Length: 126
Length: 126
Ligand SMILES: [Mn+2]
Ligand SMILES: [Mn+2]
Image (cartoon, helix red, strand yellow):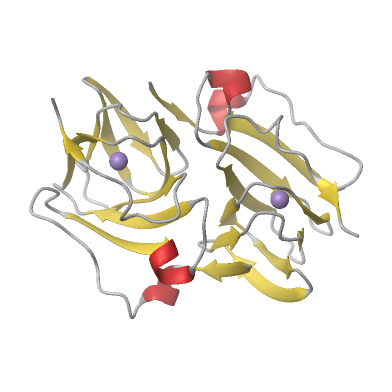
């Protein structure tokens, strides 16, 4: 089983969002609920200017691949700047946030070692 | 543990390559051999024009995100065009190849649901 996706592929999928991540939206591109894939899952997120993926963690490791714009990554309390062309490693349980303080859309893919997004349990900062 | 990487973070590291797939060269940005990361591994790879990482397979599921250029994906015999902005799912042991039929350098990231690259064994097609 092999397949290809881009944003246009999922025009029909409405965006996901939540009060807790204001200015943030996302769609699933590789996910067991959608594609019947397994082992890895991937979504595409947008953080609007002024937007904030607020400090959180979860049990699986995560990789973010930044594709547009720039932001302040919050590495469990140490701030660092990220931008298009960066990849990021977030070990499980590690608290991370990402704010878009620029004027361009901060776009990135994420990846989890799981079949589905929905099997990933989110927790607010301690 | 959280960290960032881009091409510059790994200028010190050398382009590993193999005769089995010519025009192909990669480096490891997220990998236990290097970072003491776990759960996910990521590499960045380049295929020269006329370059083709020949069809093959391996236990882990795999995600490719194409960052630049254009190519032809060998979906176990079913050939699909892919381009910058495309993500690619490939199940465990699904045979896959990828040829660069463009002039630009075909660029992409790969992700494995493994700690390191150096434990994932590549088998040739049969
Ligand atoms: Mn996260
Ligand atoms: Mn492969």
